[PDB]
Amino acid sequence: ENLPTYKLVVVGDGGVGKSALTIQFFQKIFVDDYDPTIEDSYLKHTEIDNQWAILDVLDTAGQEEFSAMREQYMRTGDGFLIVYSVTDKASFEHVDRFHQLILRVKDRESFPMILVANKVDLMHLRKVTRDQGKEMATKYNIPYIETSAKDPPLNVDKTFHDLVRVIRQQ
Ligand SMILES: Nc1nc2c(ncn2[C@@H]2O[C@H](COP(=O)(O)OP(=O)(O)O)[C@@H](O)[C@H]2O)c(=O)[nH]1
Ligand SMILES: [Mg+2]
């Protein structure tokens, strides 16, 4: 058998939940104080839709100019999660920056990605509606998913699996 690696890159503004989502996925715990500047990668064999793969995931953090790993992951990544927080309108607006960046680096008209609206467990603080998120995803022609990394987590496994599905379906 030829077991593929899917290199997945988690991008988005600071504070949106990239680390919490990634740690929830790999460790099944909610970490609420993960250093905003620390970048980690994760590697594991896992089975998605009854097909084995290796996932190599970068949880991006801090400045690109100080990152050892960023350049290679951006250039060679197979898919991207673009994460915003529904409580941070600027983070939602900035999705367009990440969308443009990915298409520029990958040098293609489209590329595997999912729009991830995180922190949907929060009601009072929510500033970006579901419909605003879904319309943005429609504009980019990419999937839209709502998540919460807080216990009990919502759609965390599904988000990573769905990105693999997009890669497989392209
Ligand atoms: N309520 C809630 N808080 C979250 C969620 N995801 C992350 N957080 C919190 O938001 C803050 C930033 O999360 P973090 O994962 O470090 O963001 P990052 O900078 O994108 O890596 C932390 O205090 C987390 O506990 C979520 O789904 N719901
Ligand atoms: Mg982080």
Image: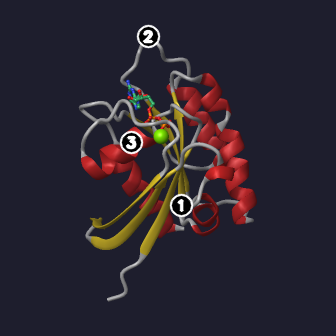
Indicate the quadrant containing the C terminus: top left, top right, bottom left or bottom right. Answer: bottom right
Q: Is residue 131 above or below residue 43?
A: above
Whether label 2 lies within 8 Å of ligand 1 gets the answer no
Sequence-wise first label, 2 or 3: 3
Q: Which residue is mark 3?
A: 21
Q: Residues within 10 Å of mark 2 (few under 14, many from 20)?
A: few
Q: Residues within 10 Å of mark 3 (few under 14, many from 20)?
A: many
Q: Nearer the viewer, residue 32 or 154?
A: 32
| Residue type of the residue flagged with mark 1 | Gly
Q: Residues within 10 Å of mark 1 (few under 14, many from 20)?
A: many
The x, y position of residue 138, in whole percent, is: 61, 42
Q: Mark 2 near mark 3, Cβ–Cβ under 8 Å?
A: no
In the shown orientation, is residue 123 left or right of residue 60? left
- Look at 48% across and 44% down and name the residue there: 38
The x, y position of residue 105, in whole percent, is: 72, 61
The x, y position of residue 131, in whole percent, is: 55, 27
| Residue type of the residue flagged with mark 2 | His
Sequence-wise first label, 1 or 3: 3
Which of the 4 quarters of the picture holds residue 44?
bottom left
Q: Which mark is residue 124?
A: 2
